Image (cartoon, rainbow, N blue to C red; front, side, top):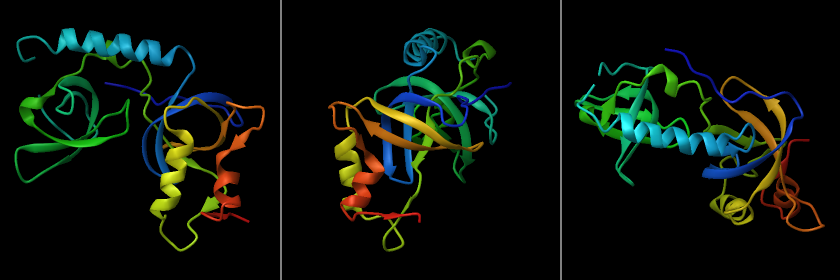
Length: 194
């Protein structure tokens, strides 16, 4: 089995929506390119059909699979993260960035044609900022949430790695462009990486 993350070129501007959110150094974005959100929804419908069959699984680290999310009762794409002392396994939901605990009956084998679409839960962080103390305050997390929730921001991909990208987010909902990182620095909630 083979799979991929969404790819970028340096300084690529592209629209995003933040789905998951833990800190300014850790959040997950859906990137609006190549009809990603349209294709992801179609994929999840296909997976509901396939995973509604007579149980077609050898759970091993880094193996792709169909995991069942109890939080809404549907099957989504996943990667095995850890195997616990119990018969339970920790998985990462690759299209959304969250990690959960599930029983072995809540896992399935994934067919190759459901891997053709890149995984869409892109790990992200704001570039050129740091924690003022040494860990992120929750007041910094809270305004970052405030400024991004249910909003379609412009992202500029400033640094690429194998395991996530560093971005600069801009809210263009008014003629005054609100660059998030500058807002967190100007409001003394984080320090610049000068």
